Image (cartoon, rainbow, N blue to C red; front, side):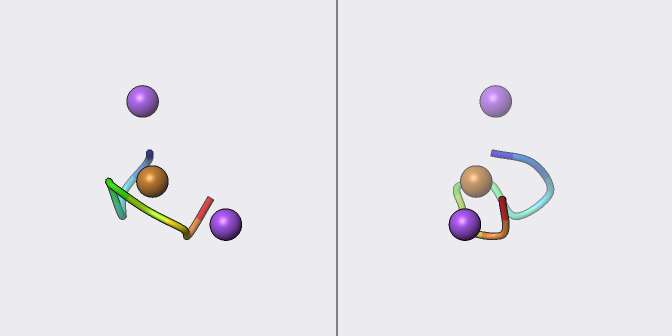
Length: 10
Ligand SMILES: [Cu+2]
Ligand code: NA
Ligand code: NA
């Protein structure tokens, strides 16, 4: 990250 920080959704 994003809205799943820390990822892997990115
Ligand atoms: Cu992330
Ligand atoms: Na960031
Ligand atoms: Na990813």
